[PDB]
Length: 129
Ligand SMILES: *C[C@@H](O)c1ccc(Cn2cc(-c3c(C)noc3C)ccc2=O)cc1
Image (tube, rainbow, N blue to C red; front, side, top):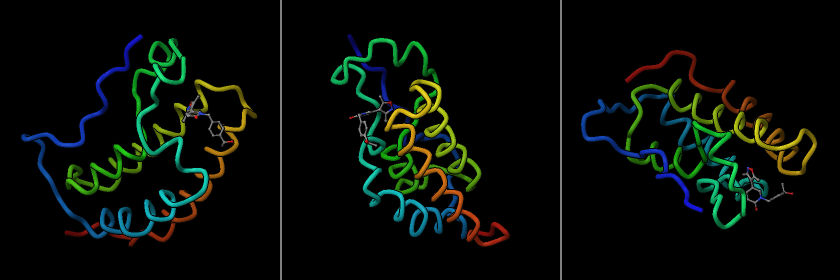
């Protein structure tokens, strides 16, 4: 079995920006989630080879994880905060699609998504450079 290449965290041609909102995503939102006791399964791409999940990447065609998001924010990969928010949403969605509702990993993801949504209500209202 093989894993796919992970999602890119840098791209030489993609315009880069640091916005007030992107800075709040790094300094607050991701800080809270990264350090939470439920974060660790989500800190790196799903390793389908080590987990013995040969169907994972047959079912999940848009992978995403918090390690990728952290590297994207540190590399100033994004133009806007909505791209980052979309990545968190993808990560949660993937967990809910692959696993059975009420598996422990799903309940953990639900708890992190609830926390995520709480924190992103405190984003600066207007995105500015
Ligand atoms: C929340 C905690 O109880 C727990 C449960 C299960 C695992 C096992 N596991 C699962 C994954 C995984 C992800 C992130 N998405 O689909 C799966 C199957 C990854 C690593 C891992 O050890 C960990 C913690």
